[PDB]
Structures are given as structure tokens and as C-alpha cells.
Length: 15
Image 1: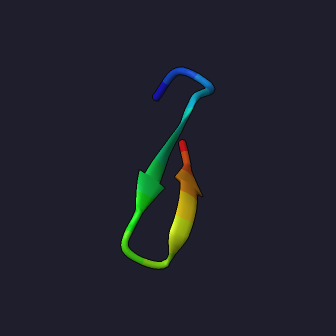
Image 2: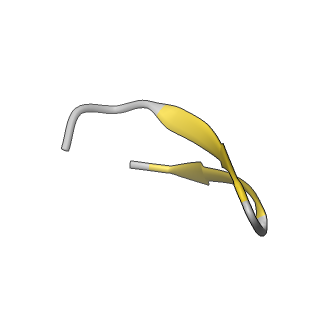
């Protein structure tokens, strides 16, 4: 996966 983060359930999760 390309480097990038998204707001997830348990805070910001990152690739």
C-alpha cells in the first residue's frame, strides 16, 4: 500500500 493515513475507529490508522 502507498504511504497515507485515514481517520479510523481507533484514531488515525496508517498504510
